[PDB]
Image (cartoon, coloured by chain):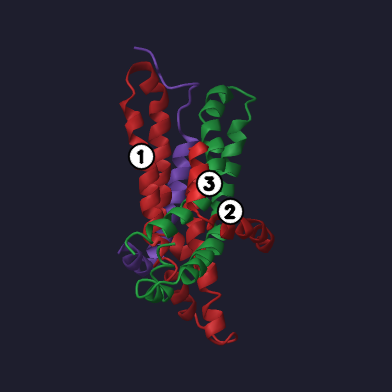
Amino acid sequence: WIIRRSVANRFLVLMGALFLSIWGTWTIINTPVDALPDLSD
Amino acid sequence: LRHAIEAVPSLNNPQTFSEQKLDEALYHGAVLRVRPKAMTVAVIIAGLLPILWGTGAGSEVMSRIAAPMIGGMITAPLLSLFIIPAAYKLMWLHRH
Amino acid sequence: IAIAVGAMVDAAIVMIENAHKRLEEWQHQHPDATLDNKTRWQVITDASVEVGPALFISLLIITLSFIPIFTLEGQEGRLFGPLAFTKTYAMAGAALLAIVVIPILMGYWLNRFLIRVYHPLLLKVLHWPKTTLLVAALS
């Protein structure tokens, strides 16, 4: 199935994960923090 | 186990009866599980182990949510290694 | 995300492993000093042939058999809510990446002695194996 169509997208998939990597790294650096999720009614 | 009994030895099994031929087919799906398995079990428990240790803020709840999985990952693999085969060799004999 | 890490790496390895032995069969059936960039291509993508479904559907299993957790109402649902979310997204990512990148990156880049402790008891399990299904029952 999809394992076939994937090998073809060899190059840009790498760059997608290249930007994704530096995109997911930017967000984590700028993510709010707290001890727990708000559990109050 | 299914593809062992779907390969070339699975031409002999559905054609005629040779318990010693299906056993040999389960012994390779046996040694071929160990390598990917022993590691899958190891990576699950090894990576799940740090949270089991409960020193620090929030450790309490994460170590409680962990133990069940780590404990369940000793008996699930250990047992399923012998329970799945001995039940697939036994269920393959009924249709047959 | 912490609890989930043990399973993301699990997605890639079982795939890579079936490839490590699939590359050791081509080595025994063919020559050993001749191979191209494409001949190394076909052997690895052929490891994704077999277990490909088994794992992706197994991670699909791991992220869905957990969904029911979201039904927790009130205070408890707000606590384990975000944990369920991330445990799910983490897998969905590792799963959707073991089909877009993982197979690619693996083609671009004492087991005996545990095997000797196991099969003696395995071959043993085929003794009136029913008796081993009975022993599992008492567990």
Discs 3 and 1 share one subunit: no
Discs 1 and 2 share one subunit: no
Chain the render paints red: C
Q: Is residue C38 above or below residue C111?
A: below
Give the alpha-carbon distance from disc 3 to disc 1, as whole Å. 21 Å
- State the image coordinates of residue C93 (x, y, percent, origin top left): 40, 48
Chain the render paints purple: A
The residue pinned by badge 1 equals C65
What is the chain letter for disc 1? C
Taking the spot 63% from the left edge, 30% from the top edge, the residue there is B53
Circle nearer the N terminus (3, 2): 2
Residue furthest to the top: A41
The residue pinned by badge 2 equals B38
The residue pinned by badge 3 equals B79
Type of amino acid at the residue the image marks with label 3: Leu
Q: Judging from the image, what secondary structure is the residue with disc 2 in? A: helix
Give the alpha-carbon distance from disc 3 to disc 2, as whole Å. 13 Å
Q: Judging from the image, what secondary structure is the residue with disc 3 in? A: helix
Q: Nearer the viewer, residue C83 or C130?
A: C130
Chain the render paints green: B
- State the image coordinates of residue B49 (x, y, percent, origin top left): 60, 37
- State the image coordinates of residue B91 (x, y, percent, origin top left): 38, 56
Dividing the picture into quadrants, the one containing residue A17 is bottom left
Q: Is residue C82 above or below residue B17?
A: above
Callout 1 touching callout 2 (CB < 8 Å): no
Discs 3 and 2 share one subunit: yes
